Amino acid sequence: DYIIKEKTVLLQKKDSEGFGFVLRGAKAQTPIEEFTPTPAFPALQYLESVDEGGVAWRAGLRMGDFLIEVNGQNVVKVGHRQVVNMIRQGGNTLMVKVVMVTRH
Amino acid sequence: GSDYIIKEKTVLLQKKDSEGFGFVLRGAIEEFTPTPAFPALQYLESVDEGGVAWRAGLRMGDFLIEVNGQNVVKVGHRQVVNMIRQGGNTLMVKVVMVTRHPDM
Ligand SMILES: [Br-]
Ligand SMILES: [Br-]
Ligand SMILES: [Br-]
Ligand SMILES: [Br-]
Ligand SMILES: [Br-]
């Protein structure tokens, strides 16, 4: 039985800083296939690391958070490259909907 | 934000010819993406108590993920219905029950 805790947070940063988090893939997907979300892995991208005291950190984001939406756009099946580009477009403002999965 | 309790269930239904599986399938634009809140396009609108589906553990609100091994998360209504009637009196379905608990 899974418990998925969801929330939408707003990240606001300065021009000379980053959002303070690193994104990686959930599993070792094969490039010849689309990602299939499951309760344990609801999104292709997840936060692999968050700098303590950084923008993402202060907003409540933590390692383990799965990325569901970027600036109102669903990115559950979207790759790293596109997500980075999407985040760039937003400049110093980034809205993300994330989920933390628990209880196995 | 909200908490989403997720319970996945895979059952095997077997019915007589003088009966149906005992459920009303409803289809949730035809290009959607699964999210923890809404994991699939088709879901059980109704399930007859004491029916084949009911006795197997299926309940109103369950989202259809697979029909006879085939992922139907993003498949249309007519197509899924055909897949179900294909197996005849036998239907193996994987579903996910989602209950939302809003934050306050
Ligand atoms: Br899918
Ligand atoms: Br791109
Ligand atoms: Br790309
Ligand atoms: Br969600
Ligand atoms: Br549909």
Image: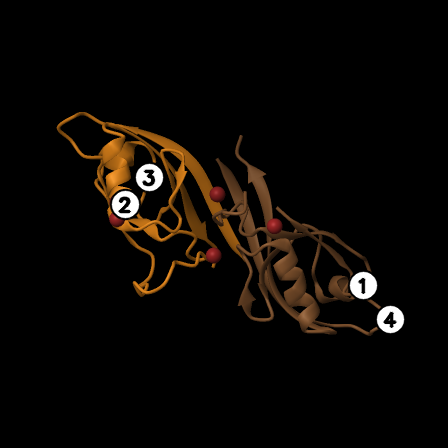
Chain colours: A orange, B brown
Q: Please name the residue that numbered disc 1 is placed on.
A: B51
Q: Are marks 4 and 3 on the same chain?
A: no
Q: Please name the residue that numbered disc 3 is placed on.
A: A61
Q: CA–CA distance between discs 4 and 3?
A: 55 Å
Q: Amino acid at mark 1?
A: Gly
What subunit carries mark 3?
A
Q: Please name the residue that numbered disc 4 is placed on.
A: B18
Q: Is mark 3 within 8 Å of ligand 4?
A: no
* Residue A63 shown left or right of residue B24 in the figure: left
Q: Are marks 1 and 2 on the same chain?
A: no
- Judge depth for marks 1 and 3 and give the one in front: 1
Q: Residue furthest left?
A: A16
Q: CA–CA distance between discs 4 and 2?
A: 53 Å
Q: Earlier in the sequence, mark 1 or mark 4?
A: 4
Crowding at dot 3, Cα within 10 Å, few <14 / some 14-19 / many 20+, comes out as many
Q: CA–CA distance between discs 1 and 2?
A: 47 Å
Q: Amino acid at mark 2?
A: Gln
Residue located at (36% from left, 53% from top): A44
- Judge depth for marks 1 and 2 and give the one in front: 2
Q: Is the residue under label 3 in contact with that under label 4 (CB below 8 Å)?
A: no
What subunit carries mark 4?
B
Q: For mark 4, give the secondary structure.
A: loop
Crowding at dot 4, Cα within 10 Å, few <14 / some 14-19 / many 20+, comes out as few
Q: Amino acid at mark 4?
A: Ser
